Amino acid sequence: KDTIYHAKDAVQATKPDMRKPRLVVFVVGETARADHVSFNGYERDTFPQLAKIDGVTNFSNVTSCGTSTAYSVPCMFSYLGADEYDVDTAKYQENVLDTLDRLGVSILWRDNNSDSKGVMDKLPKAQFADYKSATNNAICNTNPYNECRDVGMLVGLDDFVAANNGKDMLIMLHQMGNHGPAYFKRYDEKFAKFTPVCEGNELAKCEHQSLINAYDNALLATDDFIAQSIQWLQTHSNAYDVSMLYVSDHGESLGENGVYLHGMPNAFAPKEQRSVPAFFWTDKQTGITPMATDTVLTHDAITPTLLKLFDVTADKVKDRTAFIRLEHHH
Ligand SMILES: OC[C@H]1O[C@@H](O)[C@H](O)[C@@H](O)[C@@H]1O
Ligand SMILES: [Zn+2]
């Protein structure tokens, strides 16, 4: 079907031959709950490595648009926003990646989760890569499950930067993250910090604390993946203005009222399935400034954030709140 347009007015105010090119990693998270983030008040240190990195902003009031991967991911990149979003027609709308690609930003999507749920479908096929494959992902033999790890998506990104030398670049890394029910499979042994761990597939039959322990160990591995993603960006900070955005697609029920996993219709889904973490990191020289940590935010903030990071204006989101501010200190 023909593409329905939303941002044909979009203009990029500055080009990478007149200022530093910009390089952004957007980590599309999976199944992570805001209330299990240390920064949000959780009594366990689930993000020790991010805690040591300067310039990380944690956002304490972020609500997902939905409770599943197929529903939330397209909306996260949409112009319609959660209130007018239609999952069944999202694929035919111009989305924020379409706009950025059209204006010259090089887009890459690596996926260790499933796929882009239609978001990459209008862009050239080679700009999407399946990193659940052990012949794309070199980090699948570190665990007895032979499960490919999110950090494997960082291997060879330097090839992409070199192939796009001096251009603006936006790289999506779609995480396996905290996907259940087998939380215990989601992390290598070095992250088996909270013990004992539920290693059964029937969650209600595990002792509750052992389920929480497995879930929190999986968060430690995501803390590590985000920290290494920032470290990778930092190797490019002299030539590029580098930033990292993380937002989870939805949360997770962990036995409250006997509910497990996610995917429940928004009308009656419990809050645990909607309250998600978000982090923003940027290098000091970029001039990008985060919004207040307690700003009331939703997935609708993602599209204007991605546009602002590349100096793009679009009428459709002119009134939207982003994760980053409009004002600039000189
Ligand atoms: O029930 C169908 C859909 O309803 C939405 O409100 C939820 O966010 C989705 O996860 C679900 O798939
Ligand atoms: Zn998901």
Image (tube, rainbow, N blue to C red):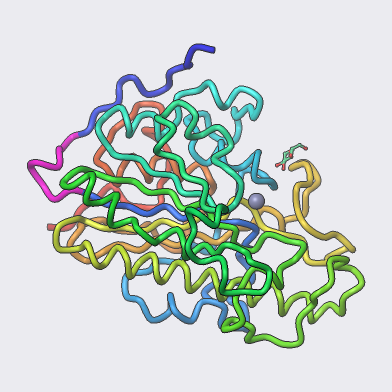
Which quadrant does the N terminus fall into?
Answer: top right
For the residue pair 39 and 216, the one nearer the viewer reads as 216
**Which x, y percent locates residue 171?**
37, 49
Q: Is residue 291 left or right of residue 289?
A: right
> On screen, 173 above or below 151?
above
Asked whether residue 62 is in view, the answer is no
- The residue located at (49%, 12%) in the rendering is 2
Q: Main secondary structure of the magenta part?
A: loop
**Looking at the rendering, which quadrant does residue 193 occupy?**
bottom right
- The residue located at (39%, 65%) in the rendering is 229
For the residue pair 104 and 256, the one nearer the viewer reads as 104
**Which x, y percent locates residue 269?**
78, 49
- The residue located at (50%, 66%) in the rendering is 139
Q: As drawn, which residue projects farthest toward the front?
A: 135
Asked whether residue 254 is in view, the answer is yes
**Looking at the rendering, which quadrant does residue 200 occupy?**
bottom right
Q: Is residue 207 left or right of residue 246?
A: right
**Which x, y percent locates residue 205?**
92, 72
Task: Tell whether position 15 is magenta.
Answer: yes
> On screen, 4 above or below 173?
above
Q: Which residues lie in the magenta part?
A: 13-21
Task: Tell whether position 31 is magenta.
Answer: no
Q: As drawn, which residue projects farthest toward the top?
A: 2
**Looking at the rendering, which quadrant does residue 87 occupy?**
top right
